[PDB]
Length: 168
Image (cartoon, rainbow, N blue to C red; front, top):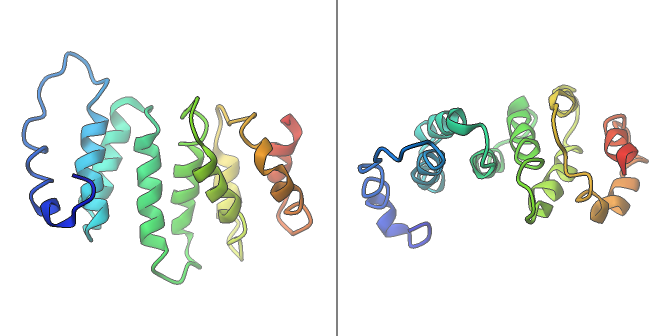
């Protein structure tokens, strides 16, 4: 039901009502994201955000929970003058959906973060939150964007691109 707009007013509650006891939380977050991302499409600012904010509490994994909150912060911050530090949340979403989402296409969100570096003026909270991650990063998957990451060396604020360059 993710397409076909008109059923989204009754596609939310038709799935948000069962929520059984599933002998383990290997799929609870994909519940609390997917109906939550039905609230991402239509303008529902608050219950999608807390639904993602509790689905991220369930496993701290299955990075589509980390991703679609990034797509929803794209849907928010594509609509306002983007001087504010509200995309630091988005770069933390794409970055902490980049590493652990393994063995599939990361080029959408990694090609997103290569643009989100250069909205940098003038808050350094973007590169501070970029520096704030610890864990795994897709060492092999940056390679395809390495021309676009070397002709972005020439611009200012490349002192965090060097962390991507150094392990390649």
